[PDB]
Image (tube, coloured by chain):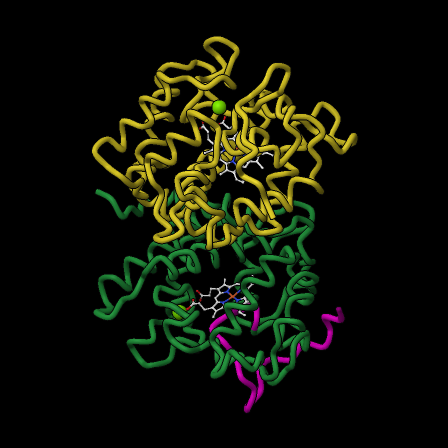
Chain colours: A green, B yellow
Amino acid sequence: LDFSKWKTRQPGEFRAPCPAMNSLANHGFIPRDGRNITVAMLVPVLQEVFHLSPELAQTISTLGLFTAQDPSKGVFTLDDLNRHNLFEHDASLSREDYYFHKDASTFRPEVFKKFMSHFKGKEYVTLEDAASARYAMVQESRKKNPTFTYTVQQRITSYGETIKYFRTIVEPATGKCPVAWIKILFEQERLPYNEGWRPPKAELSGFSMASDVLELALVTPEKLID
Amino acid sequence: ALDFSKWKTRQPGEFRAPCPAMNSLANHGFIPRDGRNITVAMLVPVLQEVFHLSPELAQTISTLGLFTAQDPSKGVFTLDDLNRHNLFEHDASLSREDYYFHKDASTFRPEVFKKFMSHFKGKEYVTLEDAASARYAMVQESRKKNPTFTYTVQQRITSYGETIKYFRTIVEPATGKCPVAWIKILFEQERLPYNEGWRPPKAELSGFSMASDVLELALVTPEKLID
Ligand code: HEC
Ligand code: HEC
Ligand SMILES: [Mg+2]
Ligand SMILES: [Mg+2]
């Protein structure tokens, strides 16, 4: 894992709405041009760079394959991940809903500003602030987007994405998530190795995700009952 | 591959847990009948085969079971180890009373289970919403009556997870729906209702799918740690 090979995205290179996957490509940990991705190649990378458990890595990578133009052929691209309402969903943290400009892939400073304002004056992301920030995007989409789609599938991916950054973009010494490293991940699509980040000591598993998603929901004022 | 007709209820000397599924496995002889000499390596394929747990989820829960032994290094645990309060066993159970009251959070309590089952009165099937209400009712009873109520991050995920476990594994092959009558058999007899039509579930219960299910259960539970 040579983190010094990093280059920002170049013309012709496919990129996704994911800052993690986009960082892998920019680091050259997966093909830089965002093409020719297989589950077999991605899974070890996710385990080594982000310390996802084997099964969680296999699961998310396969959900990625399911966005391919032909998932039978076992190959997908970062552009496949941009397909609306397959994996990509409304109420994102740093991207606008597909509805508005038919581009839910391009990083949006004005969306990211809203998200980050939930951590203003803090060096670290707390569970409660991360809950508030994600749910604020749900409320905005619900009030602004007449096509808002937020089913069982989108709910877990949305909750899971907040857990993913909260658990993986952490200080080795503390396990805590610095606001400044989130900023680097989303804005630069660089893993903040230079700033002191390393692959997490703790494994992110399906079970640990389940606990974390529960804890997020218990500090979110979101209910489907009344 | 598996013989479900070998079921016997608990016999003298045999250890049993506060878990109706682990007790059914033993009563069926799918793990050692006496509730002893359980290892992770033995239990994971049984959980995969009988309950369609994912390899990783099965490994994780089996290991949580193992860390209930006084010495996990021995690599072996028993259903009696599972009876140890606030290791895996926890307050606000659906069919057992809190350890506080009589130092017995292992023996099935008709009175507790009566209150659990009251949330499905008039219904053939368990819905996510009624399962959520039945579990939260136990949390509120424990918070109301037990001065030593313990409900930390660890108990919460296991409590939510156990409702999802019966809701997803004790289901009709035809519909994936959870029959009230089958929950009654599992809890009251500690028998998998094979005789009545139950079969290992078609759908796999994985860490990811559990995470979705626990999320959805929480979204229909009036439970928050914020107000
Ligand atoms: C392994 C570590 C990992 C981390 C950390 C991670 N992801 Fe993503 N991720 C996506 C997609 C697609 C989205 C877009 C969802 C959306 O619309 O917000 C996304 C979104 C996100 C978001 C939210 C972005 C936003 O603007 O809301 C975060 C944070 C994130 N991913 C972090 C496909 C993937 C895939 C697919 C193969 C993998 C593997 C994956 N992601 C792995 C990871
Ligand atoms: C694989 C299928 C499986 C199912 C279905 C299952 N369990 Fe349990 N389970 C427990 C323990 C300990 C409890 C007691 C928790 C409590 O205090 O309610 C429990 C409780 C439960 C409960 C709630 C009972 C109540 O009175 O609240 C249900 C339902 C349950 N288990 C179902 C250890 C285990 C272990 C340990 C190795 C395994 C594996 C396990 N359980 C696997 C399973
Ligand atoms: Mg989106
Ligand atoms: Mg208990």
Q: Position of residue A77 (x, y in %)?
A: 54, 81
Quadrant hosting residue A56: bottom right
Quadrant containing the N terminus of chain A in the rendered view: bottom right
Q: Position of residue B195 (x, y in %)?
A: 43, 38
Q: Position of residue B62 (x, y in %)?
A: 63, 38
Magenta residue check for A110: no
Magenta residue check for A2: yes
Nearer to me, A101 or A55: A55
Q: Residue furthest right?
A: B74
Give the residues in magenta: A1-21
Q: Position of residue B177 (x, y in %)?
A: 34, 47
Q: Is residue A212 left or right of residue A41?
A: left
Quadrant containing the C terminus of chain A in the rendered view: top left
Residue appearing at x 43%, y 13% in the figure? B147
Nearer to me, A158 or B37: B37
Count of numbered tags: 0
Residue appearing at x 61%, y 70% in the figure? A190
Nearer to me, B31 or A167: B31
Placement of A89 over or under B183, stated as above or below = below
Residue appearing at x 57%, y 68% in the figure? A61
Residue appearing at x 21%, y 69% in the figure? A146
Q: Is residue A157 left or right of residue A24?
A: left
Placement of B196 over or under B52, stated as above or below = above
* Main secondary structure found in the magenta portion: loop
